[PDB]
Length: 56
Image (tube, rainbow, N blue to C red):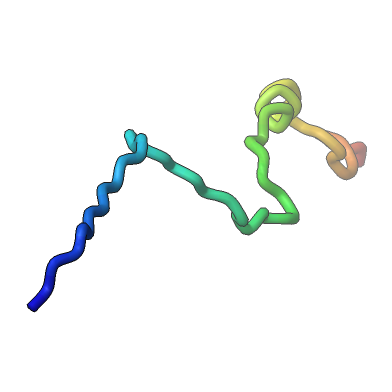
């Protein structure tokens, strides 16, 4: 025989969650060569040895 009042209900708010951390950072060089474009597309002969044409 058994007769006992046993009742249990659960109720909690829940919609959505997106937690993300602990990301490995990359060292060294991680940037677009912006200046390289301006500096590279400005001159033709930079730091060139000797000169065009010669005597004798």
